[PDB]
Image 1 (cartoon, each protein chain N blue to C red):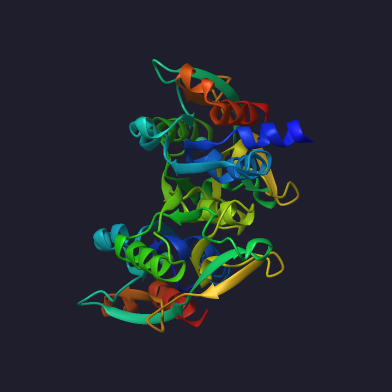
Image 2: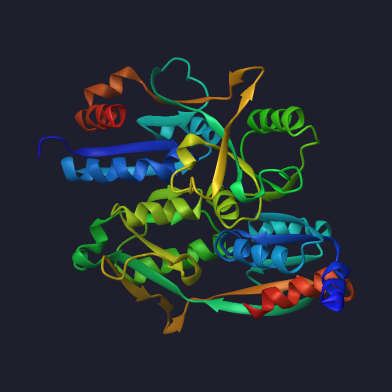
Length: 204
Length: 196
Ligand SMILES: [Cl-]
Ligand SMILES: [Cl-]
């Protein structure tokens, strides 16, 4: 009990984390809650923004968690890959082309991939008839029955399997995926609050 | 059947996430022959793109040279775990991205009421992220009423935000050129959104 408290107390100081949008909304809060419980003496600083923003501000952070590609001159730990699903009301299989497509703001390489897939699979020109700034707005539009969309798996929690059909997105019989990486200077692992965070996040 | 054609709507972020979807669902059901086009972005972005839309719905101020119908005012609440009422100053404040006048008002309130310098120890790009951080017990925040649905009254305490005994409010307006009301799909939308 003395040594348990000793270790808990021991890990302290500050950790600054930069995290991309989707994971920041869905998984980070849970991780941070667990991290505060296990390591109450460390002060957290967090930014959640687009991958591009976080990568631009890399000097602000001990650790970055981003969707896209590895960051050069840093260690990169692969956390997971995400598949993507075309989602539409189950009751409406046939006339999917007539429903508005809901587009959320994201990396332009990603959007152009989605557009391509739409062209080739609905055999009709892609048009974002509903365009939104925030992913949760996209999800709310979907859930309320207003349209169809494509979401990565991480955003698909609490979407009724009873109400909606899910079609895995593939381009030239290759699943559209995005990888998420945790990136840091390896020497930052000598800080115990950072080492602790990195192993906790990687264990999810 | 009669009411048809296209309507293009621009809407600010919070209402776009929270109320617009419901309105659009009702509007599709009542007027199935009209094709909707929608953009949800920040107030500034929607106002900048005003020529793209028949109707704008935004939080902030009226738009000049357009008709403006006041939809509702929002109060704002400081929200923290009941579980930690005492040491609120120690918890991280969660800031969502918003216009700088609003943030400066939040900062000022924090200074004068927690008697400690405001610092956004958790800053997030999207309001739903702020709400998720709050709900998971990570910190404290200030939300406008419209974003407060499904926050447990059992788990959290709510303190109305006031500056010099004046409630911090934001108004939401629907704005359009009055001549757009001659389009029945637009007239229909405007009266639905205003009644909701
Ligand atoms: Cl992400
Ligand atoms: Cl708003």
